[PDB]
Length: 21
Image (cartoon, rainbow, N blue to C red; front, side, top):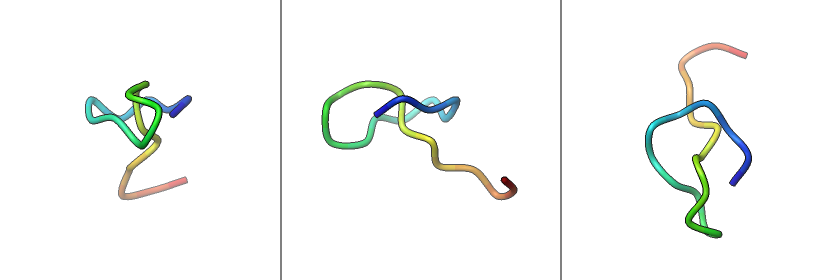
């Protein structure tokens, strides 16, 4: 959830999965 990554986390919201901070 709450992220810039195109994928989702657990809440279905944009995940914050990136290669750098």
